[PDB]
Structures are given as C-alpha cells and as structure tokens.
Image 1 (cartoon, chains in turn green, cyan):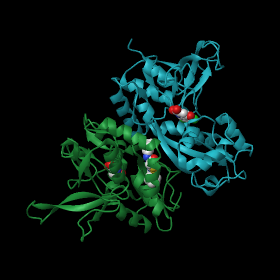
Image 2 (image 1 turned 60 degrees about the horizontal axis):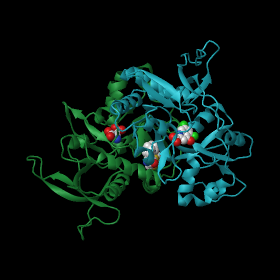
Image 3 (image 1 turned 120 degrees about the vertical axis):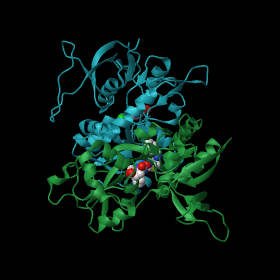
Image 4 (image 1 turned 180 degrees about the vertical axis):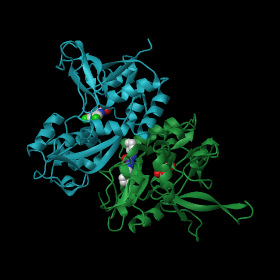
Length: 281
Length: 285
Ligand SMILES: CC[C@@H](Nc1nnc(SCC(=O)NCC2CCCCC2)s1)c1ccccc1
Ligand SMILES: O=C(O)c1cc(O)c2c(Cl)cc(Cl)cc2n1
Ligand SMILES: N[C@@H](CCC(=O)O)C(=O)O
C-alpha cells in the first residue's frame, strides 16, 4: 500500500503550523493537512484529532517526495516529546513514532546522529546543520572548546550559556563534555524564542543550538545584533534527514529523489523561498 | 585477501602526493602544533602525460582523507593498501564506441570493476553516482564559493556584478570542471555561464594566480579548496554565502559489508570532534 503515516513537529521555518481557514475547513495555498491530538481536559486522556495546516521547507520536501516517489500520506504532529530522546530506554518524539511503527517516516528539522541511526534509518541529508553558538555581537567565543564553556568556573563571573534540552545538541554536549553539560543545565531554555530574548536583553551570554535554526534566526534578527560565532562555525556538522524504519522499502527511492532535487536546482529554490534573511554575518 | 584496496586521487588538502626519500621512506614532517604528519605509502602512476605508460611506483600520501582512513582502519579493524587512480579522474560516465551505453572512468570505474574496494577521497555525492555505488553519510560538507582579492565585496551568486556581467568585473571557473557543468546545466545561470565561457581557465592553480595578478576578479570553485587557499594566501578571501551545497562521502559497492559501520564511524567522528580537528589541521591555519 502507498498511503503512509508520516510524523512531523513544528519548528519554523522548516515546519510551520497554521489554523485551518474557518470558512472552508480546507488547507489552501502552500499548505498541507496535518492533524494534532489535543486533550479535552487534564483529568482523562480523552482528546480530539484537530485538523490543522502545515507549511515550510520540510513540507515542500515532503510534497516533492510524495510526487516523485509516488505515495500519499496522513501527516500528524507528534505530541509525545519533540525531535527524539531515549528516556528510560524508550525513544520518544519523532524518532519514537518511527521506532514503534506509528509512522512510516518522520519529516522535519530532524538531526542525523549516531545513536538515532541505531534505531532508525536516515535518508541522505537535505539541510546542512550541526551545533552553532549564538551571541550578541561583540561577545567573544572561539567554538565549543572555548575555556569559558569547558571549565566555566575558571572565570569570575562564569559565562552564562545554555541550550534547549532533550535534543541532539544537549545529547552531544552531555556525551563529550560532562562538566560543561552539568554546569549548563541551570541555563536550560524552554524554547528558542525564550533564549533569543534572554540573549538580546543580556540575561544570557551564549545560546548553543541547532546550526540551521540559529543561522535562520540570525538572518532575520531585528537590527542584526544576534550572530552565530565564527565564519559560520558549525561543530559536529551533520544534516537533517528523513527518518525511516529500519529496512524501509522507501529509503532507496527517497535518497535518489533528494539527490535528484539537488542536481536539478530544486534545493536552491527552497532555500530562496524559506531560508534567506536580510542579515549576513 | 582481507586487505582492503583503497583508491584515492591527488587533491589538496585532502590528499597530498609526494615522492619517497632516497631510502624509500616518507619524510618526517610535523605541524608547528607538534604532531607528526601521518603518511602512508600509495602506489600509482607518476607520469600524467597522454598516451604514456602508467609505471606504478610507491609514493607518499597524507592529508585529511588519509587521516580519516587511518582512523577508520583502526576503529573498524581492517588493513588496507592505497593506490592512486590509474587514469587520474574522479569518475564520470563516458560513451563507448559503437554504443550509446556509458561506462564509468576514474575512481568510480575502479570501484565498480573491483580494482578497488573503497574510494577514500573527496568524492562528491550525487544522484548519478548513487545509482551505481553506495555512499557513506558525508565526511565533509561543503559547497561552491567565490575567491576574490581582499577588499572585494561580493554577496554570493546573487550579487549584481555576477547576475549582470560585464568585462569590468571578470569571473570564471575551470573549463570542463564540475562547476562548469553545473553552470551549463542550470538554465537560470545562462547569462553568467555566457560570461564565464569567455574567461574560464585551464586549471585552478592558474585561476587562483590570476586572482592574485588582478586579471581575474572572482574565481568560482569548491569551498573546501578555496578556504584552504585563503588560509595560506592572506591577499585572497572567500566571499558571500555558500551555494550549491554538497558533501563528500566514502564510496563502496552496493553489496559492501562495510557500508553501515563506515557511515556510523563518520557520524561518530563528527560528533566527538575528530572531524573538527581534521578541519583545523588541514583546511585552516
Ligand atoms: C546552517 C547552515 C545552512 N544550512 C543549509 N543547508 N542547506 C541549505 S540550502 C538547501 C540544500 O542545499 N540542501 C542540500 C544539501 C544539504 C547538505 C548536504 C549536501 C546537499 S542552507 C543554513 C541553514 C538555514 C539558514 C541559513 C543557512
Ligand atoms: O567529481 C568529484 O568528486 C570532484 C570534482 C572536483 O573538481 C573536486 C574538487 Cl575541484 C575539489 C575537491 Cl576537494 C573535490 C572534488 N571532487
Ligand atoms: N534538530 C535537533 C533539535 C534541536 C537541537 O537540539 O539542536 C534534533 O533533531 O534533536
């Protein structure tokens, strides 16, 4: 069968969620239907699958794959976690939906890393990403090995830096730099927007996060005051990839199609449409 | 045999190629930051001239790709022998006589024919090649960028002096190169290609020297190379955003029992900082 359950997660500009137009109850323009399970109340787990509309860079990738590889799909937004973390030996988020076979594939701002590749297969990367550091222009940081990150109490006052927990960036820091990581958790940010405000008003000195999202946010920052350190510095360079079930029959054709989109300039079109900003460096 | 046959190609800073010393060993070199340069013996032709015999002699190889090979070999517990691609090419499909059927040359051809078991080189991942071989996840992400003299301001491929060309600001790439083919293939770069066709150079060294000598104002080329060139030549800089992003991958045949773990090892090496260390050793300064 060629009708596929597919999971996604909102993260602008890769996946953006809109309400459906109330007069037509249809998703129009550049959007596709996507459902979200929403609870009635906090006492029971009864809920409704709410019809919404999705758009963005990764949604356009999905539309192109659906056409070229010839499948249709039922797109839903994950509500158990976010991108993916193993908690008590059980994967949640988009990764978990694929591992436990609720989704044939996961499409979104999903970082390829080694531990996820042990439990899902990833397509070729279709966005370059990794870990970057965002600061207010003027703040000096060499990279992740900067002593202010690695041995933070060697400085008075210590440097104030954090991430959004439970994603690939926190997992990388936890695995590589134990002292840094345990220091940082007091600066955990609830989301990217909170972190940007905290930086801009000087309550936080640096925000460590997915390179693609930070480069996008730097590109649209009001006044071009928040920047990623270095000459587009990226640590642990990787990509967003489509996650598929181990052994998936869809992987080969998805890989070839993504690589065909690159060769034919289609990827450059999506960059122009979704990823360009007015700030540069 | 269990020794893997590795094929590579001369392409700095990924693979340097030098003669052995008079006793057949490779010269001791270091970096100012201390570490001995790790070198491997690679056999290959040492006469490029057309119609020449391909006399295979031991040479010394080192660089980003050789360090990567050394690490993989140790991590995955394999032995290897390295040779330089006999015809000197990365790999394109060319026509046979009497047939519209194509055949791969270069490193692709050697991998497919069994003359190699693994391509360890800066081999661009693309659709055409992936139809025939398996690639790892990328060991290096890169793209096209623009080399100019310091002080020259160019935003990238959408800069007005690129999109609306004139002989007041000359830009160009290497004839018949992957970049030239890319500019030919894309219809929307037609006015730029027409300009470049009047000015393209025979080699990257020649283009890069022309930028130094103010005869070429911008050279369009692979960003890994151009960042390396900028790192040694302080009068030259890259400029603008990367475009036509791409990645280099290890190449293996479809049936290879090494493909899964080679790719996991590359992911591991990005995540633990090994790849960043290679970048600072070979691509920066
Ligand atoms: C964070 C740096 C930058 N990352 C990007 N990745 N891809 C684009 S364009 C889309 C594209 O070429 N995909 C194909 C590539 C994907 C990787 C392997 C080769 C084929 S920009 C970025 C992101 C967001 C805003 C500004 C800059
Ligand atoms: O066909 C190719 O793979 C190819 C082709 C090229 O021209 C390459 C150049 Cl200039 C530099 C580097 Cl680092 C890699 C290259 N790869
Ligand atoms: N893209 C990341 C989430 C953001 C981050 O942790 O940098 C992931 O897939 O986990």
